[PDB]
Length: 231
Ligand SMILES: [Cl-]
Ligand SMILES: [Cl-]
Ligand SMILES: [Mg+2]
Image (cartoon, rainbow, N blue to C red; front, side, top):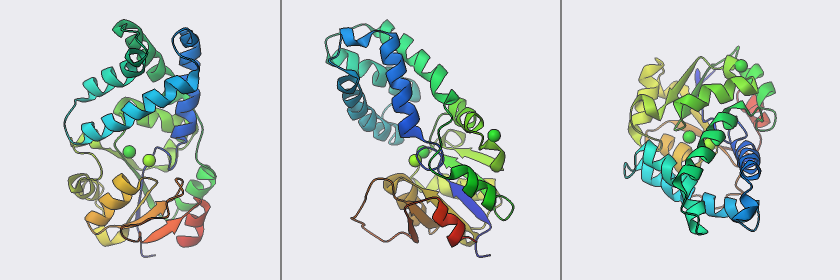
């Protein structure tokens, strides 16, 4: 086999982050009777997402700390509707973090695909997500067992797509570059990052992307395609 090491992103590649996070935010929204402050959950969540997206970029650029990232992203939607209650935002975030890692939703066919690949490849996670969440998410969903090691941006202090985290992931796992494949849903973090260091990439397209500044090594629309690609 050409590849010996498969590096998977976690969120929206293996774990159903968008689905699981929407469910969790809605549960916490309802718990705190947020219809008092917003027209609907979607009024809340669209505001939350707009700022959260901006914030994760600032974080990757070293413009906010993880702590400031978290403080701002749960407070932003409340202050956007005139609620200046920072303590309420903090209680909300505590409940979000208590619940999110308990969710078990995976991307389609993930368990089957991982069970198929595990005997034949070293399987790794390469993720920017929080150490106190990532392995818990994986256990809850029953997929932690497939992965030999989890490599986090927090291990190094550098987020995808910066090159350092990819070179670190290779060394940390005794992996040769030419024997490694990055599999992920983020064009900007996973595919651009891996391409940047000369590592092959399989772009898992769940955003209906049609425009490519460069072509990924492989372009798949289902994790099932991995079983065919890497048979
Ligand atoms: Cl990530
Ligand atoms: Cl597990
Ligand atoms: Mg992802």
